[PDB]
Image 1: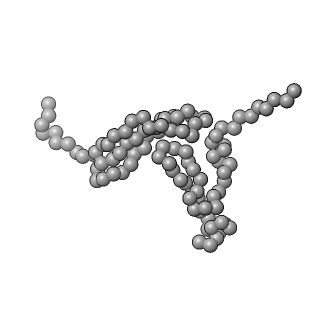
Image 2 (image 1 turned 180 degrees about the vertical axis):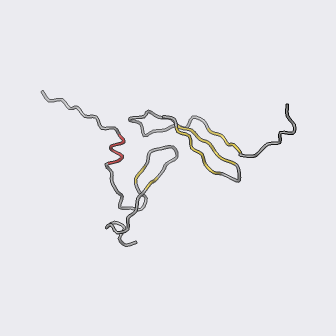
Image 3 (image 1 turned 45 degrees about the horizontal axis):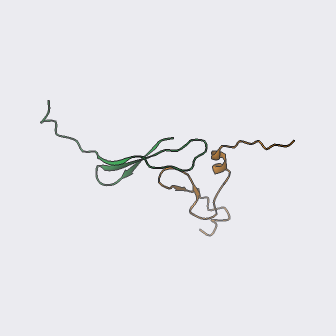
Length: 49
Length: 48
């Protein structure tokens, strides 16, 4: 009799988004909207830089 | 979850705005209070 149990804090969801191809970055849900981003130009999505 | 934001506005001045939510789940904040403050040294020669 299968029932679904699971509990992942939304922080884990916000972490599993990983890097971002675009230069806007991923959202840190806090106060006035805040767009964070990490860049390593050697990678593929920012290689053109 | 209460979070205060401090925004530089002018020389000395600053802007303060607050927000709240539920911690483990909520991505939705709703501003509860706000105001402006200024970091100016006063004149304590009219005092007591």
